[PDB]
Amino acid sequence: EWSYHGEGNKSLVVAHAQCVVLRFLKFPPKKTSEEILQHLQNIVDFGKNVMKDFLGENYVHCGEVVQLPLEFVKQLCLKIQCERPESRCDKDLDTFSGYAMCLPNLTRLHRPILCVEIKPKCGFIPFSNDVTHEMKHKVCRYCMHQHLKVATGKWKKISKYCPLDLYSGNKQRMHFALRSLLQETQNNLRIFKNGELIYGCDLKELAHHLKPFFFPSGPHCTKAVIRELVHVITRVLLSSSEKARAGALRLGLQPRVCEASPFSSGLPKGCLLYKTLQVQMLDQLDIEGLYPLYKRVEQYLEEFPEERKTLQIDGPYDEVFYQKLLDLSTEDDGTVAFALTKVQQYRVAMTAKDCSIMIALSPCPVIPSSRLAFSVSVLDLDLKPYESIPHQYKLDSKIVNYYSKTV
Ligand SMILES: O=P(O)(O)O[C@H]1[C@H](OP(=O)(O)O)[C@@H](OP(=O)(O)O)[C@H](OP(=O)(O)O)[C@@H](OP(=O)(O)O)[C@H]1OP(=O)(O)O
Ligand SMILES: [Zn+2]
């Protein structure tokens, strides 16, 4: 009755054939049942108390936490193991707790429905005066990283996608980047049709499944069937129902073009990319940067460990947590309070930098112009842990220093 639907390293999704999925956690071969509730509960809290503000009520969809029979979680886990990539069989499924989270299936909701999930990654190159390496002001994080992934053997080759192409307003750049994602999908593009993964774990094999959409006789080459996708997706990304209202974060745009991008005024105010980009800007300092402040908070919390709970570090992510994030002032007064605020803003921006966007297309409310009804949603919105900020500091040095070798 349930089927594998995809995963990352934090969670696993399985779809109901008869329109809801289930997000299951995944640990190695260690936590308690009490612990796992709070974690999942915080993700719900965070979503509706923080992200629902930053990205709008209809973009962020959440569903409540559920409890299920423990034998039933054992009886699904064994079936799935053949479906899961060998890469992600390092970590096992959350089988013991019996808890899971139920999100509505965006792929499903007679209706032929095409779905494009993107993991756009970071849309800006850092501007902060904390950055010690020169190359970080010229090249984006994504483009530098790509090197170390291919040298590691995570992916077979370099991607020509730069996120700044996609996060720029320009349709010609946005098309190029979308073309570049289709050539090297990696974990940045997946395409679904009627609840089924049809692309990014053959350019011409895609056109077989997409011909019935954009041309419902003939004759249309793959070049045509692919170009409509690129154009439709670009229009839906430049779509907005809120060109007027003032956002929560009014962070000013500060570089517009990456040096590494092989290609050749701004994003619409209400569009999901623009709202996603603002949340990412909360990293006003760099990690270089934010890490000194992390240690300032850390040494305080080690002096006073009961403070970790009372200062809402790992929860609750409630209406007061939200309001603390609003203080944009960047000039350091040497306090814990200042250092703590920036640590929480970074974690939030860190979560906006790893999130996926789900674009649904179906004919048939709202339309790019037969004329295709569309919805736009955002995913992977659970807060990055406080504890992982040192890992991000160390990883930042490695990407830059290795890429700097390659010049
Ligand atoms: O497993 P990957 O496809 O390589 O993706 C990972 C993963 O994100 P997903 O689980 O959503 O796929 C990490 O997120 P966590 O699950 O650990 O929270 C994230 O790590 P951080 O947010 O801690 O940075 C990391 O991003 P990054 O590479 O920027 O460190 C990102 O990897 P890539 O996007 O680089 O593939
Ligand atoms: Zn780039």
Image (cartoon, helix red, strand yellow):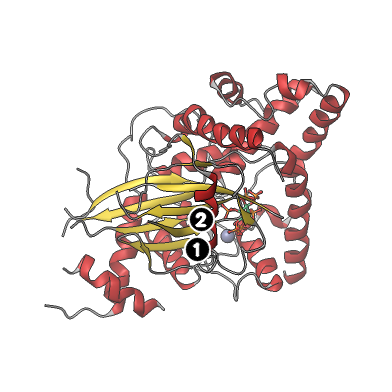
Q: How many marks?
A: 2
Q: What residue type is labelled 2?
A: Gln
Q: What residue type is labelled 1?
A: Lys
Image height of 399 relative to 130, above or below: below
Q: In which quarter of the image is ligand 1?
A: bottom right
Identify the residue shown where x is 51% and y is 38%: 278
Contact between labelled residues 2 and 1, with CB atoms less than 8 Å apart: yes
Between marks 1 and 2 in the image, the one whose residue lies nearer the viewer: 2
Residue 169 placement (x, y as % from top left): 41, 51
Q: State which quarter of the image contains the N terminus.
A: bottom left
Q: State which quarter of the image contains the C terminus.
A: bottom right
Q: Is residue 317 visible?
A: yes
- Circle 1 residues within 10 Å: few <14, some 14–19, many ≥20: few
Residue 25 placement (x, y as % from top left): 58, 47
Identify the residue shown where x is 21% and y is 70%: 212
Identify the residue shown where x is 65% and y is 44%: 127
Quarter holding residue 178:
bottom left
Which residue is tagged 1?
A: 79
User: Camera-side residue: 169 or 378?
Assistant: 378
Between the residue at mark 1 and the residue at mark 2, the CA separation in whole angstroms equals 7 Å
Image height of 328 relative to 191, above or below: above
Residue 305 placement (x, y as % from top left): 82, 24
Image height of 141 relative to 295, above or below: below
Residue 159 placement (x, y as % from top left): 55, 69
User: Camera-side residue: 112 or 321?
Assistant: 112
